[PDB]
Length: 38
Image 1 (cartoon, rainbow, N blue to C red):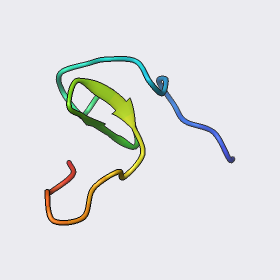
Image 2: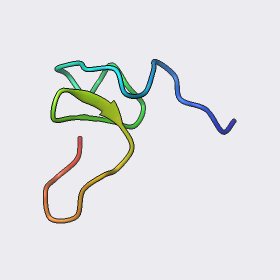
Image 3: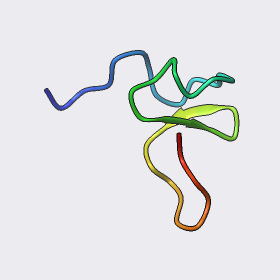
Image 4: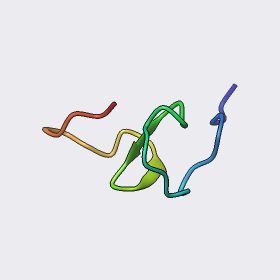
């Protein structure tokens, strides 16, 4: 449903531990444009 799987705003290193994208050491949504996600 409208929810994540692991957690958001939590700092991590591998994007895998998050359905969205763990960018700059954080589990967040697709906050990017030219930079690739995961």
